[PDB]
Length: 195
Length: 195
Image (tube, rainbow over all chains, first blue to last red; front, top):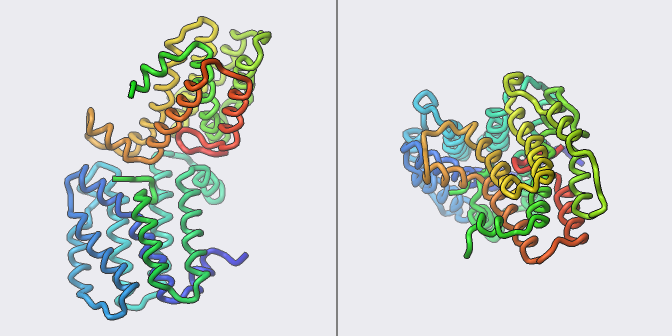
């Protein structure tokens, strides 16, 4: 088979944008949980941005002020210096993903859209590695990380998402709706958070 | 409905023993992973003990030297002072569960068998709480812990296991075999470890 990233890069811009939107939606619970527990920020800023990202995929007539959302997103991005709780990290990653995707859409920067894949997977590795405190490196570390079900799920979800998008030469309203509904109805983040 | 622990306590000794054996089997990957990564101990000591616990449920004619296994188990129980890696904790819990169950069988101590439930669930809470570093207590902490899919899975697996045992007035060979096969074929621990 061709490699995951060669396949991701072979997507059209709209296919990439769908993939990355779906991944960003999946991270939301992380921000929600952090915000509630650490009494920081406003999750509605992220959900509003998400709804506009979904609509951008349905509705070619859609226009909105990206910069104002980027600014609100940044205002709601926490500083790790300010929190002892680990949740600051996935929360930051969630808002920063949305910001990166909106910024990439604005600049038609396909690389950044593709890299939302790595952001999602790194959040999961960092979670696993946060606790572990092992001395492993390189392939041995990789195997150790993948022995954890949450990482295997990350891999499986990103692959399954890629497969459904790639079997469709163009994105369709039904495809966008169905992926959004699936992600939102599961309501479990890339690191297993549900609010 | 009646409470989980009232229902667990209402089990017969053999029903309890089955429940606890199944939970101990499920923890094995934790010991295996730690042992391999931290180059400590011998997982075959735990799997040998497990196979004898399974056989004890099939075969009323079965006898063996419990104390010698208890001693081998203790020889293979790591000291947290000796390891920086977090895995020492679930590994310890895995071997200590098996030791507690064998000890309870030897003394017909139903309480200790029932408490294998708490050992299993605490391993999962400690894993979640290890990373989190939150200030929450009491019910708020409980809700925070249950927002993590691994804990919800722990609850669901322990309930489902209890339900299948409790709907059978006595344990049967088919029941014991089927639970063992299910747990071993999944090969995912209470904290999501697969080797």
